[PDB]
Image 1 (spheres, rainbow, N blue to C red):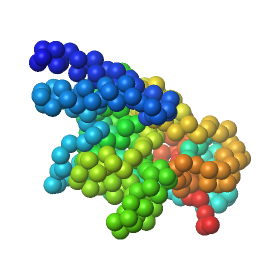
Image 2 (cartoon, rainbow, N blue to C red; image 1 turned 45 degrees about the vertical axis):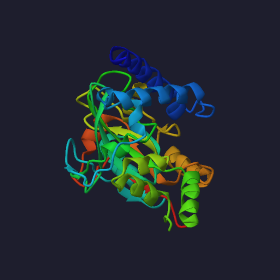
Image 3 (cartoon, rainbow, N blue to C red; image 1 turned 90 degrees about the vertical axis):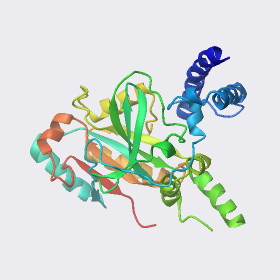
Amino acid sequence: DRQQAERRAAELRELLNRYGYEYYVLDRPSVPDAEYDRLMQELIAIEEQYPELKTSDSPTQRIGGPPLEAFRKVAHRVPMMSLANAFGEGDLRDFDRRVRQEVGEAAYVCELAIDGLAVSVRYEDGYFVQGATRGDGTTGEDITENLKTIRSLPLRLKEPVSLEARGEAFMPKASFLRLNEERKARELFANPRNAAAGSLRQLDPKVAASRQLDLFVYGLADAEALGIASHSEALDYLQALGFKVNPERRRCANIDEVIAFVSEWHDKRPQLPYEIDGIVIKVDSFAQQRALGATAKSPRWAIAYKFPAE
């Protein structure tokens, strides 16, 4: 058994890891998940008698470990700048005009700005080693055990690389509704943003695990050191490794299409399973970014369109 335990937990780990990618990430259901579940129940039982084989990125970790009675501060690897806000066609034009004066027409990448909790996740050789909140931007809290419960985040990546990436953790609308009712059956959350930040900022891994959190990876700290030369190449790269990258992202040749994208989400937004706050726009090329630089506050190559005032 102890020699065979390892063998089978290792198979177990591989298969479960594989299969969680197709449910949680590609969304090839997560419905009749039987064998998945059968397979998870066997790993859990093997770790029950051989607690020493429960690997830090074993699928078991999504269940969640024991509470912590404290969280540690973490500064740990590259500042997390915040973005300038835009509120109308026009802040948008003005944001492009300083783009053009300095670099000529520049292609943009437009993304949906998710209303959630910003986090950083770090990996070493493919392994998830640490998770943290945005904090003030230079320091945040180690929320690693609660991040392991977000089933779409990978504990082990497709290739053994060492990197740090940034994503937004959120809770889907219907999950938020579900949630609150039971809270009413017994208190009550304001909205998903505070539900997710709430779920991630409490000390008990298992209550995180029960809130059905999700996350969308949106950037790569130090992408230049890894050889990436474009914002669109960063995400793609991130997608090739196994991360969940929001698929409504689109490359925009100029401000006009930028605004066409911005109008398209403004009214297609109610139909989303998650709550979007606006639209983040970035100059795609890392070279135009260098040229525009920053005001060590806010990149001149990025703006955050904040949607309106219902």
